[PDB]
C-alpha cells in the first residue's frame, strides 16, 4: 500500500547534469550523531546541477545518492560515490527534512 508513516524523514531531490559534468558538491566528515557519523555538505559550487536546485544548501545532511545508502559509510566513500555521478546525467540527493522548531 501507500507507505506513509513516522519513520523516514528525508527529501528526494533529483537533478539533471551533463555527461561528465562536475556535480558541484563538497561534503566533509561530521561528528554529531549517536553511533555513527553523518554526511554534511561543507561547500557547494554556486552554479552547478545540485545548487541550481536551490533547496540543497551548505549544511543539509546527505543520506544517499542515486539510491546509494551512504549513511554510516566514511566521508571517503561518499567522496568516491559522489564523483561517479559526474559521468551520469542525473543525480538524486536525499537529505533530512526536519521541521522548524
Image (cartoon, rainbow, N blue to C red):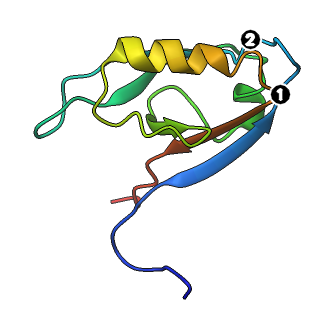
Give how far across and how far down residue 35 sits, in percent.
Answer: 11, 37
Badge 2 crowding class, 10 Å Cα cut-off, few under 14, some 14 to 19, many 20 or more, is some
Q: Which quarter of the rendering shows the C terminus?
A: bottom left
Q: Quadrant of the N terminus?
A: bottom right
Tell me the tag on residue 89: 1
Residue behind mark 2: 22
Please tell me whether residue 43 is drawn above or below residue 38 in the rendered image: above
Rendered residue at 79%/17% (across/down): 47
Q: Residue at x 77, y 24 (%)?
A: 88
Q: Secondary structure at mark 2?
A: loop
As drawn, the residue found furthest toward the right would be 18
Mark in the foreground, 1 or 2: 1
| C-alpha separation, residue under disc 1 versus residue under disc 2 | 10 Å
Residue 28 visible in this rendered orientation of the protein: no
Q: Is residue 54 above or below residue 3?
A: above
- In the rendered structure, the answer to whether residue 74 lies left or right of residue 11 reads left
Question: Looking at the image, which residue is at 43% across and 40% down?
Answer: 69
- Where does residue 3 sit, x and y in percent of width and height? 50, 79
Disc 1 secondary structure class: loop
**Residue 41 seen in the figure:** yes
Amino acid at each position: 500500500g501507500s507507505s506513509g508513516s513516522s519513520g523516514d524523514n528525508c527529501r528526494e531531490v533529483h537533478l539533471e547534469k551533463r555527461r561528465g559534468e562536475g556535480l558541484g558538491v563538497a561534503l566533509v566528515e561530521s561528528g554529531w550523531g549517536s553511533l555513527l557519523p553523518t554526511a554534511v555538505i561543507a561547500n557547494l559550487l554556486h552554479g552547478g546541477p545540485a545548487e541550481r536546485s536551490g533547496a540543497l544548501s551548505i549544511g543539509d545532511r546527505l543520506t544517499a545518492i542515486n539510491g546509494t545508502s551512504l549513511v554510516g559509510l566514511p566521508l571517503a566513500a561518499c567522496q568516491a560515490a559522489v564523483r561517479e555521478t559526474k559521468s551520469q546525467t542525473s543525480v538524486t540527493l536525499s537529505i533530512v527534512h526536519c521541521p522548524p522548531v
